[PDB]
Image: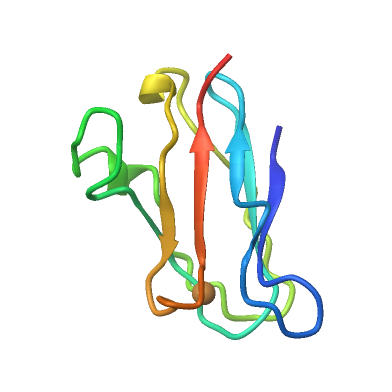
Amino acid sequence: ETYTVKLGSDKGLLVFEPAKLTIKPGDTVEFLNNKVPPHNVVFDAALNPAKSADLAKSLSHKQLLMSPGQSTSTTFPADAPAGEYTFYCEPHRGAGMVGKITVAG
Ligand SMILES: [Cu+2]
């Protein structure tokens, strides 16, 4: 169900809460900006079950999470080869802004 993955945690912490998410075969996920902007999430160009790009960046979304309290509940299809995908926050590298969804059942 649209579970919320916030981009940062308490007063400072700039991580993915949660980070490793096993959802359903075609569930809904929520992306909320918590700290230091802006956050765009691109998917597994390199790390996905059927090593493709085409679809990977057709799942990942770029909505420049920049305003303090920006939550975008989004949904996936029911095929998404039921594996551990990987979404990273474009301008925030080093500072662990990366997450994984398992579209399994
Ligand atoms: Cu970020």
